[PDB]
Amino acid sequence: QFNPYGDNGGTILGIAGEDFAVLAGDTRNITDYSINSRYEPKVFDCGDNIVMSANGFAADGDALVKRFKNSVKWYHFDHNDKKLSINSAARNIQHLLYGKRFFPYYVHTIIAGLDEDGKGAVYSFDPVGSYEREQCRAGGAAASLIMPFLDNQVNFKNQYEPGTNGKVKKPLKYLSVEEVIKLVRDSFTSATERHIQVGDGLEILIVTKDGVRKEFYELKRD
Amino acid sequence: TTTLAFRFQGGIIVAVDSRATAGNWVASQTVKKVIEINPFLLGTMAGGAADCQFWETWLGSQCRLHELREKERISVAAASKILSNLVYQYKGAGLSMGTMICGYTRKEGPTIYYVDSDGTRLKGDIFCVGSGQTFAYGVLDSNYKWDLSVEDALYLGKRSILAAAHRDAYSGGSVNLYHVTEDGWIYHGNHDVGELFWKVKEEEGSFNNVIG
Amino acid sequence: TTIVGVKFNNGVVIAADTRSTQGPIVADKNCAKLHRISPKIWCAGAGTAADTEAVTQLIGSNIELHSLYTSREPRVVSALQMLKQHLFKYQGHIGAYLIVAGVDPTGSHLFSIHAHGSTDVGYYLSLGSGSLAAMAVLESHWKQDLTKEEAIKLASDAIQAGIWNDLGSGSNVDVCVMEIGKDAEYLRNYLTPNVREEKQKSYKFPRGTTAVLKESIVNICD
Amino acid sequence: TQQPIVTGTSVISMKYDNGVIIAADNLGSYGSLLRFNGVERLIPVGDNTVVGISGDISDMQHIERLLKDLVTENAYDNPLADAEEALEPSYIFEYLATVMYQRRSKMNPLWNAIIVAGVQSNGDQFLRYVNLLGVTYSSPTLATGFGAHMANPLLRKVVDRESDIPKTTVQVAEEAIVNAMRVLYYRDARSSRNFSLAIIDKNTGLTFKKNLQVENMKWDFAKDIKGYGTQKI
Amino acid sequence: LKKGEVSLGTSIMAVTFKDGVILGADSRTTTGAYIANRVTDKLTRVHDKIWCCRSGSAADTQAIADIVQYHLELYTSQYGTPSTETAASVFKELCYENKDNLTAGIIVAGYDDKNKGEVYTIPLGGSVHKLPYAINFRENMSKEETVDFIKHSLSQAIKWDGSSGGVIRMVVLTAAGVERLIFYPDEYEQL
Amino acid sequence: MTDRYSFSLTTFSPSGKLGQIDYALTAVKQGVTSLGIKATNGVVIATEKKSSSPLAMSETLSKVSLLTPDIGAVYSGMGPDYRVLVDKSRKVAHTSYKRIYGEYPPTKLLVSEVAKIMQEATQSGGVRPFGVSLLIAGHDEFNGFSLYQVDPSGSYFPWKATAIGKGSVAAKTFLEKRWNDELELEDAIHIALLTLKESVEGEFNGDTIELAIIGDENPDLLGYTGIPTDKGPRFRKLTSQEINDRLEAL
Amino acid sequence: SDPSSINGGIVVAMTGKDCVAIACDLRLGSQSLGVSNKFEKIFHYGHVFLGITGLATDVTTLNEMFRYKTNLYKLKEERAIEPETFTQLVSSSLYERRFGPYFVGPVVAGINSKSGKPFIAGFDLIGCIDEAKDFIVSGTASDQLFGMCESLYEPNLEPEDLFETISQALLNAADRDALSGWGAVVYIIKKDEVVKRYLKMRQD
Amino acid sequence: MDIILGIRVQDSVILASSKAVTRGISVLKDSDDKTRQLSPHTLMSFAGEAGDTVQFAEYIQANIQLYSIREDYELSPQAVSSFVRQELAKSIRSRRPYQVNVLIGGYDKKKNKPELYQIDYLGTKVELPYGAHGYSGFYTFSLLDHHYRPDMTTEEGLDLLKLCVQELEKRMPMDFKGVIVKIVDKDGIRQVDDF
Amino acid sequence: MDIILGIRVQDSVILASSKAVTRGISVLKDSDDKTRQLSPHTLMSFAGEAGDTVQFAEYIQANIQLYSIREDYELSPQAVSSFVRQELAKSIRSRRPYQVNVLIGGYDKKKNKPELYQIDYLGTKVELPYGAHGYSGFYTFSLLDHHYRPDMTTEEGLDLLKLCVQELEKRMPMDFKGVIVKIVDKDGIRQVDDF
Ligand SMILES: [Cl-]
Ligand SMILES: [Mg+2]
Ligand SMILES: [Mg+2]
Ligand SMILES: [Mg+2]
Ligand SMILES: [Mg+2]
């Protein structure tokens, strides 16, 4: 029987800073045990300082991104070129996703940008439209490997202040864009070692008030 | 997932956990399971996240249109029924929802309705929904009184979620509290279960089975 | 897995990759897929890892005992026959896909064995999830009258094809060369083209970070 | 919901310095039977694009008609149909990829795997894949079916990454393609010796080669092979 | 036939002629659409001048052929050279009694000095059928005619069947001895 | 039909003697002299090759046998009984140890398994005891070098040096005078050849004497390279030439 | 109805400089219900340590089995078993039940009393040995542990440092697994002393 | 067979077991004692598949009683619980496994301590301060976790047990017809007749 | 939704309906009124699939109330029961049928007679002296066959009903948390608060 879904592998990662936000993702596209492409981008600049990735089944991810990009375009037409806030885009994507509640987009969606106060924002979605704002979120095949590491290094979970008898937690603080990119790179090289669907390359999209910048890094090709 | 809501002298207490799981994998510990429908109405999330988010947000839109047309606050009865009638239309299609619609009005007083994706709509004093509902019911049933103070009632809701968070694998993260009064709801913070457990263990003397 | 076998002038050579998967997870990044049956009879194995080791050790044990009984050096056909008859008996439930090769008083030999008990003869063979990538290389570059050095190159190239292009294969290249009139030389990690790059940061924790409830001395002595 | 009947196997392709190459055998199989031997699975659209299709042949013939009808429709009220407003590979691809995804979303797919190979108006090389699920991807080398397992590994030895493309000539690229097609004849049970090959160059344009044959094969070593193990005679 | 296991196709034949008998076959072996071996030898020796053609499961046919070879070696030690009919009986006895677990189609061909060339076919069920030939033939053909008959016949099978291909192997059984023949694609395809 | 001998053929006599074991030991006494000497860095085991006929090739008949790469055995008594014991000893080293622990058994435990087999022939139904005494020399990592004697009863004793068979009484006396705890392997080989010359009557050379050692590891005899931990067998059978070299400086 | 994920739990083992470490959570449950917070999954037979994850009845059964087998090994060999040898015993014993396996994920850890070399090893449920220099992981949060260990781990750590690394690998892995947690224990093993520490973690 | 509870207090072990025996749409009996005395100071309650429960319990009982006669000595609760576990561990890989879950409440006379063991049908043994089988744990564990203290008296344990039964009677869908309660201590085993 | 009973006596109809609402392993409510007043002298109790029950009952209620306003006239119990049956008869061949069983107790003012109608989800209507839905009839029908008389008073009917509830409470596996009883007669509909 015809199965309309597939798994194109890959994994994505979105971290939010104080005055910036990053959305990273490997560039490997796969089916079963074969490699389709070593460089097939899946993190996109959608306009209005919003970056987006829909990881999972690539056909659904491409369609969703394509629809949201088009949603941004029509928001400008209908509302006097108003800028689409990250929170408004999130709610719009919920409606795009839930509109197919009974034939879902098989994707884990993450968007990143800046909120209306200029602070970094990351939103993650399930396949049918439940969403939540977060400081940190990994998605895709190797999310299980990466995410507990982020909890430990970004949000400082399980780390207590030395000498305090495990009474005083290690204090939360914003990381620099440089420290974040280190965690991203180390997250993806670790995932590349232990996950077969993760590798080839890593593309990071950084978002500041100045605009959207890209950064690319090689990964192991085995 | 563990969500509870009960009526008492001072209104309604709503307490929920924060955990989301995809199999054994813990996807999130920071999930907002109380939906702020409007400043006067709350709704709990259990079953489908999207189904509860989407349709209880939609409910808030219908409630706003009602008070614009009728120039009067919508009743909890009417608000809950708009939601239950909607999901009944979709019956069979596969929606998944188990929620408590909570509010406090003049004509009704504090009111809670359990609404459910197979069309059920029940009015009641105490409701608990989720994988850890049974653990929470135990603490509630044995300690519940109508004449509870707001301080004590808030703690009871907090302690009941903690009981579930401890035993139920699919419940945990943090506890979110709400107090619903006639003038609207008041948020009573986010409480990490990790820190809360040890605190409660020491102060209360409970959980002797656990070494700390 | 990717395993190959190539015949040359005065002997035979087999090679294999070193990745061991557990679904999409890499359990072992440097596992040994080359097995010793006798001193000059070696076996490369793909499929169910526990089965390839258990079956090659059992036959190797019985071959050693046979060699002592007969006062003769073991033959490859003896290993071949004992293996296929064992595999056939279990009707494919022992998921062992093997490439058997070696030298004996009769000459140099190369065979393949499938889990169901079928054997094949050839000058070049490949088995595993990366067998198609490897065979593409072998069919492109193989020729009659290869030298030892040409055969090792062809073999390790065929394995590389699998490492890069097959997700089930990865890490390093193991080789074993069995030449006539010589001791068999086992080249563990003959190639290491997948070395992990330096990490961007050291995640060594300050001492006392971890909260502790109790401490106690364990008595391992009598 | 369908099930394919008469099918076409691997379609392989690769980029080189000035253009792209694409190839596919002339066979239409029927389960295990090699029934139709005069099947052209490479379809030129204009003088700058070639669409290679594998999978169900009847769905392939449907797509042929769509592309043919696309060229006609583009010439309507278009004085620049043979110049600026002529069809590009990127237009032709996005059309098919739209159709393929719509059909799978209606649970009535076109049981195909397609590779659009061509050269854009600005001289850029185009090479992109789309299948029955509407899944799209691009790479220096692309292949369908068996080609994905056996051809890609060989073609990636020539062009392992983007930077290797300017270093690769048409003579080298064509040699890799023709070698790959021989390997598929050896090892694909659903393949034929006869095949077609197309080259789209930004300077020399579209060269379409029909009635090619796999040659320079190795079979002599077979005579030395006897039995399955112990047999000496 | 077990899923994923190696299949031997079904393009095999044996033809009796004036001087003896000739066995013929292709060389293709599959696992789905993948050709696992393109230079397979499906013509197997069970005795000096008794050979067989294997079809169906490669594992099953190999295990049987090995057992038959064992029985005929032991027969010869005790009772002297066996008949082609005896060889076919042992094959059948195995294929028939284990029909539930096997997928083996076998053609047995041999040369006696009394009986001359004989051919026995043993299909899936485990039945035996003695024939003049097995897979427009004339009785008492010459060696050269019978070769061309097998060559032309298998050539067409390869042309239309994807389970068949590679080289055409043939074994000639006569009083002279045993002769192995081989024919490559460039020769037989353009017939 | 069927083996109806399900009862013991070895039984206690009124005096408390187990006749068949005593008679088996008598058969060992008649057997050709063999001996074993333990050095600090090795063990040596030796015996005379009593040729049944000069037309017979004494090379084909091996009185000294490899059991594991690090364990060797020699005997006095009935050759055929020894041969089958070696077959069983080799197999039991695999089935009851190597296939479980992935490594060859230590000398004492292999000896224990052989002793068990010989004890069973003393008590089980319808069998006679083995008419041989074994000397088993071996090495293992944790016990080092060792030498054991095994009797028809199944009793085994560890020895510094000993002899069994025809002229064992005189040979043991000779070894008592010569043996010390500072002997090197080459010294033990020398003493072994001296001790054996006393019991041997006819020709005394590398073709009539069989001699093996448990000593250093032999990488050249391993048959392959590439695994550092695998360094080769400690058992080595001395060649006819190697024996004659030491007989000149005797 | 997946035996390896009914009771839940995890084990991780790491090598250091002249030391090894092995740690486990303390949970035992029946799917969603937590039943015990004292279920230790690490055992020792002399100086060789064994951690076992999987179906709890098989964990208990295999401990009793290897206790049985090592006790007899010692009586006959007149010495305690070493890690390399014990590893082969575990593999043998598991494959003996090849077509009716114990649903477990064992981990061996210890130091060779003769050579002084640190040794760790892991197995699948039918006894495939995974020998490793760095670390071994087992359990319901094995993916999580693989991610923590692969990033946090570095060679030649000292006992006091290795403790923090393995403790943080375990804790943060267990917190992203619903079926793991409820306590933790870490064994730090040196050539002739062994320290056992109970960690403080969130109890949800 | 449904509800079996166990609470270990300072000086005793208390087992509570439901009285209902239901088959199809009819409650056949409402006074069923789901327990057997294994030895003077060891009591085992049980729940699970019909027939298997009693057959298993009596088989264990016979074996422990046989041991007692042979050695003129009472086996410790720990020893009994290990024996029971092994039998269930054997059972789970049999042709037809015993589908029986048990609680073993005993008083160790040598240690002068009460002991409660929880063993499921798979042979999963755990020593606990309080235990339950089936859905029983899902409504009582939170109450026991909160009010339970390790230094409680037998009388305090019975009040704690009453609290659990009340909660079960309130929230459990099925009518289990109350419980039979038994106490195990230094003086042996006795039944609370009024509960 | 489980137990609904009905008894027609001399001068009234008595409906008894269980108070329990169970979902999964939890009794969510123990005071549920499984009935709606269709008109001043007509009462309908209901049981069946969750959601469908109340949705159906209220839909019928609205339609009968609409009729009452339009004609300024109360429809007879027989007329109401026929309307209800037809709606269920339509329903059973729909895309998704109402899985609801009902009892319609009414007092016909023109005839001066009480009337009890039993209608299942298929649209199977029967007029009865006493009725029940589901497995409830399995334990009470033998008691009503035995003890029921057609000339009974309302007080005798309530004692007969108590006998049925007692038997259900004794033999039914599920705890249904007692019943709400309502009486329909010439003076209309009233609830018995103490039962
Ligand atoms: Cl074959
Ligand atoms: Mg990788
Ligand atoms: Mg929990
Ligand atoms: Mg063909
Ligand atoms: Mg957890």
Image (spheres, coloured by chain):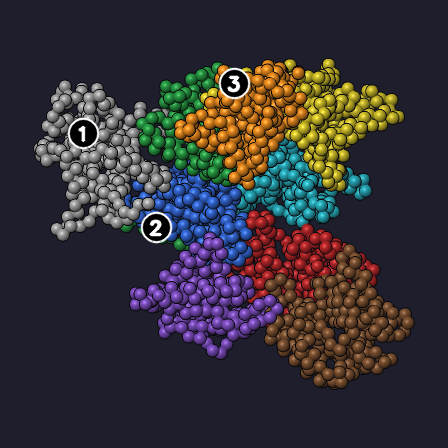
Chain colours: A cyan, B red, C green, D yellow, E orange, G blue, H purple, I brown
* Mark 1–mark 2 distance (CA, rounded to whole Å): 43 Å
Which of the 4 quarters of the picture holds residue F195? Answer: top left
The amino acid type, in three-letter code, at marker 1 is: Thr
F6 or H68: nearer the viewer:
F6
Q: Is residue D203 visible?
A: yes
Chain bearing mark 2 = G
- Considering only vertical position in the picture, is C39 above or below A46? above
* Residue F245 relative to residue H35: left or right: left
Label 1 sits on a secondary structure element that is strand
The amino acid type, in three-letter code, at marker 2 is: Tyr
- Considering only vertical position in the picture, is E122 above or below C207? above
Front: mark 1 or 2: 1
Which of the 4 quarters of the picture holds residue A90? Answer: top right
- Which residue is disc 3 drawn over? E174
Which label sits on residue G68?
2
Chain bearing mark 1 = F
Establish whether labels 1 and 2 are both on one chain: no
Other-residue count near label 2 (Cα within 10 Å), few / some / many at <14 / 14–19 / ≥20: few
Ligand 1 under 8 Å from disc 1 Cβ: no
Label 3 sits on a secondary structure element that is strand
Question: Residue at 76% across / 85% down in the picture?
Answer: I151
Question: Residue at 58% across / 16% down in the picture?
Answer: E143
